[PDB]
Image (cartoon, coloured by chain):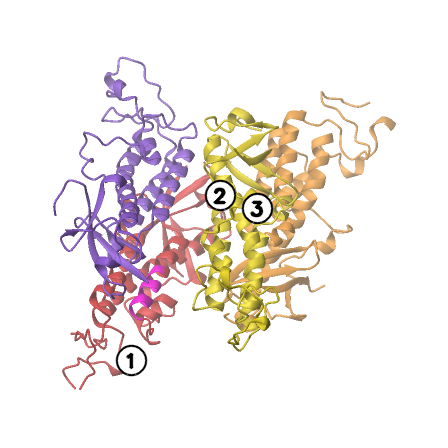
Chain colours: A orange, B yellow, C purple, D red
Amino acid sequence: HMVLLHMKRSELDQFLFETTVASTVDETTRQMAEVHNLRHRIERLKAEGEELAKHGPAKRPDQQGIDRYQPVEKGPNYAEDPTGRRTGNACDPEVAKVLVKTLEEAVAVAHKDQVAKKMPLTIKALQEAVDNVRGAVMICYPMGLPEWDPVRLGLEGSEDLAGTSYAADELPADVATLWFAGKQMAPEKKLSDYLGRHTKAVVKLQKKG
Amino acid sequence: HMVLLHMKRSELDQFLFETTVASTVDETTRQMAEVHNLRHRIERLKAEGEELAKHGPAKRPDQQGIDRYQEAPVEKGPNYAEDPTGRRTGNACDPEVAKVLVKTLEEAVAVAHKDQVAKKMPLTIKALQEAVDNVRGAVMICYPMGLPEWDPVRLGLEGSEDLAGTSYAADELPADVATLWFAGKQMAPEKKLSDYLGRHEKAVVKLQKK
Amino acid sequence: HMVLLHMKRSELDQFLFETTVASTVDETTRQMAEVHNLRHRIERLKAEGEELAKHGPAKRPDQQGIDRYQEAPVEKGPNYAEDPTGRRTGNACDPEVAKVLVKTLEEAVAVAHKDQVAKKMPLTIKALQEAVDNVRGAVMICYPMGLPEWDPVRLGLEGSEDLAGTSYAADELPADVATLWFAGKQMAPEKKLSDYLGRHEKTKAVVKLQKKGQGA
Amino acid sequence: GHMVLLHMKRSELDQFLFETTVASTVDETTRQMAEVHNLRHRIERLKAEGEELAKHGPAKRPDQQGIDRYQPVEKGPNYAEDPTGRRTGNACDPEVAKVLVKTLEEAVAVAHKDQVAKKMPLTIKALQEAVDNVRGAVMICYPMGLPEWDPVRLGLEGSEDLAGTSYAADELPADVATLWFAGKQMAPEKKLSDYLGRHKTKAVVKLQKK
């Protein structure tokens, strides 16, 4: 039948996942890595999405700097970014509360607290939460965001996490491995070959590097 | 539109409940009284079930007394453990199957605990009733003969306790006299929740009885 | 000990009910009367619920008439579908949520169905009442404003229908006039079921609900 | 999040409706629909075999088949000689058999092609629920259980061999299932919207094997 897997990397990096106990390690590793990467995308969307809500679109990374120490185009809802990373020309505050709400919902869908609530995560639920944030983003900035905006990159899965503290979080499908009781399950074998056809199992995602 | 109600009587006597803001006050009050009564059934079920797990079935209420000071010789089974309160016979199940009962009681308490409010988890009648059914199932594995009609665990499992004259009667809120209170005033049963909370706004409320 | 009672009025009007043989006839008769009346409420709820599903809320009974020739102006909503009988407004819920209502109505019929006897499944008051509660919930999902006071679906969910003067009055067995018969004789309400059926018999017992003032 | 109604049509007897979000990949839709398809055909096989089990009891071991007359046989209380010689004849009591017979009809009805005309989409969960109900009826009527080779037991467990049978073409393992629309194969990596639009839509499709 089915097995309930508990991917636990840390007390904040963990989720539950349900699948066929007859499925390959290879297929399970890829599905859970896609879930894992979606969770951490959602965490980053919330930090950047809230900055977008306060201060509008990102400046291009080579053009950062705090506005006062520079001619500036000030729109109706202008709010100077103290970090100099966004233009300051935020959306109207009434639609901004909608954007903040879809971000809070998305984080809740993927939060570690879901493990206590015995709720397994799926790729489709995480992708659906990301799609709602995209919809809110299009309401507040119907023009769309620039190509370099971390919010846009997060919604598209196109961020480059190289050189950040977040690179270790990312587990690309081609190097993701799955470990149980401190040993690597071989991708070719079936989950039953390690766990039997008979309750929850703690496992851990890792990357070859 | 949905409303999240926070029934708060005290820091341990509280829960969340979700319903349509268009529902009548009366039907919400009845539904929440049933949720409330199940919570207190489960708390009593936990204290009594743990006594059942350690000491076996209840003595009939008129025949209580500690086994050693009884003129008659107590018929001691394999897992006999003298109840120091003299309320149960002492003839408990095997201690390893007893862990099944103890565990289902702990789960029932968890389903209904005040801790679920912090976890933002609303309670439902079916979830609380289902936890009681699991305790029933554990009881039938630990005592396959069943319990006597007077055993508080059986009565709790059945909804047949008589709490009159006890400290537990103030906990019980029968559907026909339960009331619902908001911002320190009693909501009228005829009205809809919307008449007090808006069509699209959480609301702290309080169950009381007439 | 327990007894399995087989209430059989007809091949469509029949159900199983299980109780302690030490129970009085009177209390068993009332319990079975509530089961019986719920079964027939559910059958009526299904006919009216599907009409509610297709055509929205009931017109007030004094203002019925087919929409096309109403003279009074008809408010056509997104899901307007003229009721060919002129009994409902036509303003149905969205059809994709309508299938939720239709499904709980079919589920209700299945809980109370005659087929439950062949499956050796006894009905209980609480299971049938729960099926009614589910149709209520689907109803409030499809019509969040609620139904008017006169809508037969609403009257069915509330158990407040008036069957006087209708074809359904012979079906209804109010608890205070319900009687219970076994082997062609009326059981006395004061007696225990065991007084007629024994303290232990492996066979079920066929009985029949009737109302005061009938034979067999 | 828009929804699409899919109509899988392989023939006028092999067809069902299926609902999902049009943003879903072809691959996951192909996989979920293959499971619906295989469950549909399991239930049809369970009905033919379950009804033989209802009339004639458990299957003889496949190498030991033969009509009882052409042999000395142990005749039980409800013995009814299987004219095909495939089952022992020692069926349960015929009125308890009605539990099985009615449950099989319900399961067949859940999955029947007629549900397409009734605009009713099938789900994996409803079809597995019907199978579980057949499991329950089976064990009310044969509490001793069925032998390992009984096709009813194999149908309930999903462990049949359809290789070399009329049913082999019916089986669509998820790993080789393809999905076809307007006479062409949809690419698994793509989204359903890429073929059917992102805006409330119905599409006839077809499951096939590589």
Callout 2 environment at 10 Å: few (<14), some (14 to 19), or many (20+)?
Answer: many
Residue B23 lies, with reference to residue A46, above or below; the image says above
Q: Secondary structure at mark 3?
A: helix
Query: Is residue A119 at all visible to an observer of this figure?
Result: no
Q: Name the chain under label 3.
A: A
Foreground disc of the pair 1, 2: 2
Contact (Cβ within 8 Å) of mark 3 with mark 2? no
Horizontal and vertical percent for residue C159? 32, 35
Residue furthest to the left in view is: C215
Q: Tell me the element at label 1.
A: loop
Q: Is residue C1 visible?
A: yes
- Relative placement, left or right, of D69 versus A112 is left
Q: Residue D10, position in %: x, y?
A: 31, 54
Going by the numbered disc 3, the residue's amino acid type is Gln
Residue lying farthest to the top in this orientation: C71
Q: Nearer the viewer, residue A138 or A35?
A: A35
Task: State left or right for residue A203 relative to residue D162.
Answer: right
To which chain does the residue with label 2 belong? B
Residue found at x 21% / y 83%: D74
Q: Which residue is mark 2?
A: B34
The image quadrant that residue C30 belongs to is: top left
Vertical side of D14 occupied by C54: above or below: above
For the residues labelled 1 and 3, the Cα–Cα distance comes to 50 Å
Q: CA distance from mark 3 to mark 2?
A: 38 Å
Q: Nearer the viewer, residue B208 or D17?
A: B208
Q: Which mark is residue D122?
A: none
Q: Secondary structure at mark 2?
A: helix
Pointer 1 residue: D61
* Residue labelled with disc 3: A127
Residue range (magenta): D133-142
Determine if the magenta segment contains residue D106.
no
Total numbered badges shown on the rendered structure: 3
